[PDB]
Image (cartoon, rainbow, N blue to C red):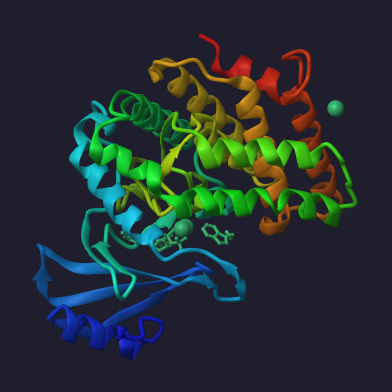
Length: 361
Ligand SMILES: Nc1ncnc2c1ncn2[C@@H]1O[C@H](COP(=O)(O)OP(=O)(O)O)[C@@H](O)[C@H]1O
Ligand SMILES: NCCc1c[nH]c2ccccc12
Ligand SMILES: [Ca+2]
Ligand SMILES: [Mg+2]
Ligand SMILES: [Mg+2]
C-alpha cells in the first residue's frame, strides 16, 4: 500500500521509510497552487543525488475540488521522463547562453505517484512579475520572450528530427497529456455560455482542436507553457539582470501540434497585455514570435496559432479573474471572433494580422 503524500507526516514517513532519506523536519513546506498535484519543498540533512533541497510532486487521480474531473496519475512518469530528456539535450535546447533550463529529475515512484526533483530555488514565477506593481522591467520581458521563443523553436525542431527515436516517441503515448487537453477544450462551450455566448460554430471548432491533440504526431510540445509555469531567477542584489529561466510542469508533455505551445504562451501574453501591462505583454509576445520564427525550421501555421490563442482566451479568461466582468466578456467575445477568423477565407483577422506583423523579418 501507498503512503499518504497529501499530509506532512505521511510525506516525512514516505521520504524516510520508503527512500531512506535524512529529512530536516523543520524544512518541510507545502507549496501552494495545484488542484491535481500536491507539491512539497523538503530540506535534507544529507544530500540526495547531490541535492540538499528537493521538491516532491504527488499526482492525484482527480481534482481536489471536483473528484469527477478524472486525470490519470501516469502523467507523472511523463513529467519525469520529459525533464530527463531535456537535461540530456540541454546544451542544444539551452542555446549559446544557457539561460533557459529545467529542474533535474531525481526519482519517480510508480506506486506512490511521487516525483522528486531538484529544488532549483525559492523563486517568483513570471506570472508574479507581470502582475506585480510596478511590472517586470520591459528589458527583462523582451529577453524572456526571446529566450523562451528560442528554446521552444529548438524543442519543436528536434522533436520533428527525432520523431522516431524511442526516447522521443515515448511522449507520443502520453495519453493523459492528450486527454487532459481534450478535457480542457471541452470547457470552451461552457465558458462562452457563462458570458452569454451561444455560438453554434463552437462545437465544430472544439472537435477540430480535440482531433488534433488526440491524433497529431507533429512535434514534441512542452504542453503547459504559460507564465504560471515559468520561474525567473533575477540577480540577487541586482533585481534588473535575468540569470535563469526555469520551465516547470511537464506532466502534459506529448507529441502534438506546434501551435499548441504557441497558443498557450501567446494566449497568456494576450491576457497579460489586456489586463496587467500592455507593454510587458506585447514586448514579450513580439520577442517570442521574432525569436521563434527565426529559429524554427518549419513554417508557422498562423491560422492554427490564431485558433490556439482563441482557445486560450476562452478557456482561461474567467479562471484568471482579471479586470471587470464586462471587460472579460468583451475579451472572450474577441476570442470567439478569432475562431471565426481562423476558419475564414483570408488572413485579415485582427489577431492573425498581429501575429504576422510581429513575427516578420
Ligand atoms: N523543481 C522545482 N524547484 C523549485 N520550485 C518548484 C519546482 N517544481 C515546482 N516548484 C514550485 O511549485 C509550483 C507548482 O509547480 P508545478 O510543477 O507548476 O505544479 P502544478 O503541476 O501543480 O501546477 C511552482 O510554481 C514552483 O513554485
Ligand atoms: N488550471 C486549472 C485547470 C486544470 C484542471 N486539471 C488540470 C491538470 C493539468 C493542468 C491544468 C488543469
Ligand atoms: Ca463565422
Ligand atoms: Mg503548474
Ligand atoms: Mg501541472
